[PDB]
Image: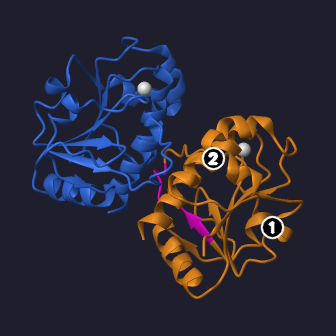
Chain colours: A blue, B orange
Amino acid sequence: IEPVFILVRPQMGENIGAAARAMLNFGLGRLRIVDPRDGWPNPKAVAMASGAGRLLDHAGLFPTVAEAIRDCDYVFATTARGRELTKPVMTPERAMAHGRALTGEGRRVGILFGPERTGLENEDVALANAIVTVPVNPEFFSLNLAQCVLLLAYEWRRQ
Amino acid sequence: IEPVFILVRPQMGENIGAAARAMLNFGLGRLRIVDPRDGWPNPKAVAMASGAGRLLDHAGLFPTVAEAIRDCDYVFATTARGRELTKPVMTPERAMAHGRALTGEGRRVGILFGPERTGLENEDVALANAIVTVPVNPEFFSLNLAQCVLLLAYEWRRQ
Ligand SMILES: [Cl-]
Ligand SMILES: [Cl-]
């Protein structure tokens, strides 16, 4: 029913908590954490999440991206630009529309988000079905992890 | 041509700089600052803006909301919930669609954003033509100033 938001190697607990708040603004609650730099549970994530702490309590903790997507039927990978990696590349609008169609059919949808400073590696994206790219100023990109999560959760809710 | 983003009594320079980065991600560059708490120019805003510093250099500084909107044909006021204040209340999607139609006709459009901790006062909203409300979880609202700015700039660019 809900897509799962999957944070890949997040670096700072505060970013994890901020991502969780962004989701919950739009009534989304399914989070997974992959191979976090600072281990887990993370009291800084809990602090920053505040009222969204329950998202963190129920987030699956996974050692690898492959394990985190094993039960997904379709996986989107978010990237700053439309990388040429053999995958289709959709805007958040066209991606979440496809996502809603899949979930309406009873399929499980995952969305990968990379660490704030580097984004996903090509090898992480290789595991996904499709790339999602926010249409951005070619001269300036400044979306942080929570903002990326916010935009996707926002598009999901828009419908 | 571009809508003007108008920050009303912003409290912390870092929030101003973060708002400017959010705009510039979507190629938007028209900013106004109304009656800021810490005065202006603000080296903390400049620091946080980084590559978006030019938005801050060209932002008009105004003593009141009335002055900041004097040259606008149509003003949207962002609020967390759909306040009953005699104005129409639109989602960001329907608001920015109307906004694009107005600017396409050569009309000047302004968008008001309140201080991060309180939002706009009813007396600020009284000066606007319409309210914009992000559709949000009734149980949880956590959009900060930069996120609010990000969502509107994102919707503007979407079209
Ligand atoms: Cl991170
Ligand atoms: Cl503020």
What residue occupies the far bottom of the structure in this picture? Answer: B105
State yes or no: residue A72 in magenta.
Answer: no
Q: Residue at x 40, y 53 (%)?
A: A154
Q: Are marks 2 and 1 in one subunit?
A: yes
Residue type at the position of mark 2: Ala
Q: Residue at x 11, y 33 (%)?
A: A71
User: How dense is the environment of label 1, judged by Cα within 10 Å: few (below 14), some, or many (20 and up)?
Assistant: many
Q: Is residue B117 visible?
A: no
Upstream in the sequence, badge 2 or badge 1?
Answer: 2
Q: Where residue A101 appears, x then y in whole percent? A: 16, 59
Residue type at the position of mark 1: Ala
**Quadrant location of the C terminus of chain B in the rendered image:** bottom left
Q: Residue at x 23, y 46 (%)?
A: A131
Q: Which residue is mark 1?
A: B68
Find the magenta span and give its range. Answer: B131-138
Chain letter of disc 1 in the image: B
Q: Which residue is mark 2?
A: B52
Q: Is residue A129 left or right of residue B19?
A: left
Q: Does residue A54 lie above or below A43 as drawn?
A: below
State yes or no: residue B134 in magenta.
Answer: yes
The answer to whether the residue labelled 2 contacts the one labelled 1, judged by CB atoms less than 8 Å apart, is no
Disc 1 is placed on an element classified as helix
**Quadrant location of the N terminus of chain B in the rendered image:** bottom right
What residue occupies the far top of the structure in this picture? Answer: A39
User: How dense is the environment of label 2, judged by Cα within 10 Å: few (below 14), some, or many (20 and up)?
Assistant: many
